[PDB]
Length: 446
Length: 94
Length: 50
Length: 49
Image (cartoon, rainbow over all chains, first blue to last red; front, side, top):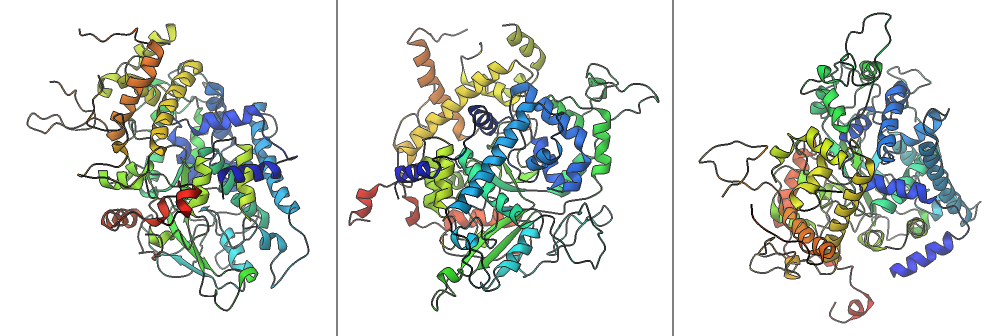
């Protein structure tokens, strides 16, 4: 399957369909090959771990942060996450943000929507068998069996294990089968060093937590479809396989989060805004070593005392610890026969994992491997560069890793998985455009 | 070219470059600048210039990478440096 | 020679000398020095001591 | 390396991946077959492969 063939077939597929403006594409570039992306953004992404309540709880700080980050290099941020940018679009649309960033987000999201529409178009509706929709029987991005690399609420798993019903499913979560998915974990039950197979589903905005209440998905069916298409298209579309996914360590992360140096402002006086005032949180007289304020000041971002106080409400809900999820399935009825039942497929994914843009190893501000440990599970997301963050990093491992993507067997062998090496080669070595590459990859996924 | 020395000049190096592109001469300071002096404290155009230069360098490194096959080493020496001097540790910068 | 004081490390006198950077340091520095710099100078720059 | 699938060992994935890392140091006895995808059609269809 020549690369030129893939590009041309994508070009045909993207004949009359939408494309991004040069502004958006150059912005997303400037973002991704910027190694100087401040890590505190990853920190807040991890701590909120895609909870809609968490997002709704931090309006002011988030808007001021994205503002100051953009009106300093015209670079957009937060791009990797699936469950924040659309949260911005849903909520941060009154007009408070600069029109350029929100327009970029709108353009990219409706482009993703048009990709979904394209997948709808080139299939025929009305052809179901054994309870499977034609959409799922044609493409893999629409089959709820296949999952995204990163999952933060078990709703996708709920869709998966309600969907197949004929494919024999098997889920391994640190050995023993099955999950429990206890939601809305507090301070009194943090247990960062917890070994059980429970899952953190989050706090639904409109509902009652309870204890015997059965788990409820936080979103609809096609939310997962958008997640899968976004992850498997746009990120490979721009990173060109440079990015990587990995886990975090809340046991050391959370303790660093309490350092708040907000001053007890005198009552009924206007809050300082410019950083030059010692009363301002960003000012040096309120700058103390080993604190969140210096973490921000490294990124040179102006923030207000109330926004920093908002973290005290933020710590209402905790995130327990990253884990590995292995899902196995049989081929669907489209390829179901007497000899392929045992002939199954497996896939590994990260729960509460996170993806960073470009590996960096040359900063004195933060030591190596302080918060994150590089755990990629994808031929697509191979990150031989990121492996330098791993403890006990040697030379032989690095030199041999350039020519093989290291994926642990408990996370999925390449041959038995969906994404194989050749498509990774294609996405990493096709240098034609970006919209064309998006369409080519999308067309591949049949 | 020592980062301990570099990380103590933030202020003065900021004002000098802001008043003045410069300091493009040797490797042992430009990428340090983009590593630490790289959050927009300076006028953004210079940051773009430095970023473009460094990404160009690593892109050429990618070029030298993909134009050889991997996994053939001898005498305990890596495959890729068997392609070019610029990739071989036996060679030294001037 | 002078190695320059390491940032994250311990001073010592008998403590063995340690590199300040990884292997990509050398290749990136070499590429930068021998390719873009001459292409920008065309042999107009010069190297000298202090 | 490309056919074997293991199970979670009830850990924080820190020790797991690290141990897998040194395990992968000597697990490779030769060049994996699925690495030379950079080859074009010709030498691919050549009888040597």
